[PDB]
Image 1 (spheres, chains in turn green, brown):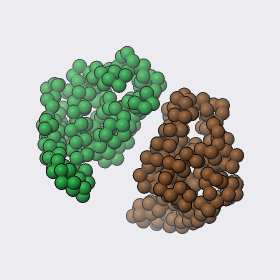
Image 2 (image 1 turned 30 degrees about the vertical axis):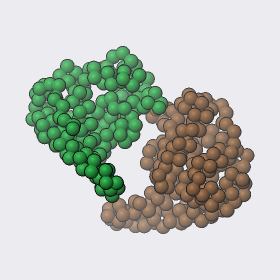
Image 3 (image 1 turned 135 degrees about the vertical axis):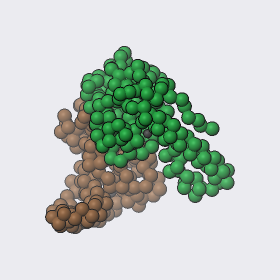
Image 4 (image 1 turned 90 degrees about the vertical axis):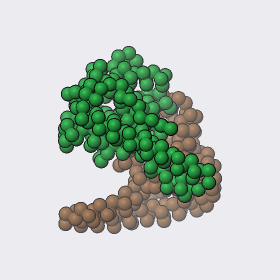
Length: 197
Length: 197
Ligand SMILES: [Mn+2]
Ligand SMILES: [Mn+2]
């Protein structure tokens, strides 16, 4: 069974950029609900599959992408954030960023653009393209996970569901986007990128 | 007002790779129908737009994308083929193919896989990514046009609707894919590649 990962930090470790009320609801309520519902759906899929009930397997897909993706996306998200974070990466990651996007600041414009560009709920991603051997930016609707739906390996995700910012920033998503750059755990992103090498 | 372009060759020019019956049906019936229905939809949209009828506008979008995309895609497709075609391209395009995909043979596998990979009706495309400055393979469902939905600039299209091949190859879509390379007009895709730069 899948379980709720602990936050690597306190609910209020990201203040003042993401306030503690958000962090607490986002983790203990939204993420918790995805894990529990995933578990339920996986159990129901076990039965459908054993019976060769194809109709039921197909009927269960939305719940499985949504709750499974919910779990995958937030689990990556918490490791992407840190009180020790902000700034710019170093080493190869930074050179790949300059190489594929021109400059770190050009990269930030792009990921922000994708993230701001999401109509409705969704996520902006920095991913790695294993076929082409380079970095790539992508956006996903609702809880659709990056690797499951595109093949890109996720490096850094930014959650632009309204629940991820609305208590602090209301309708002004680009203020949230501005703020989050200050808490990005470039340590972890670099780690994920070295895993693709 | 849009019109059906003449074919650059005669209906039997691509034998024995694509037979004369397919070409004549594809051009004089299928493309003609997209053109006809595009003209009709565009006029209706003009009316809705001048009445500020957003409902009617939004209700016309599937027809506009389907018939518009059909017109766009087939227009490109006819120039991508030639009775004098086949072989490999030369100059920069060939260099970009080697740089972006490794070799011409690997590129060919990648375009084939993406084309075979289409479930239902659609197109495989070789495209150009402006903001990244490189070649990029994509696939579009139905008549969704490459640029309008994806931003990539079309260089080479491979129609994998069943009408593109079924009378001659039936269900064996890969044999059609193996055959079409004998008639690719590399001169035209080169031009399209030089126009991007
Ligand atoms: Mn969320
Ligand atoms: Mn067609």
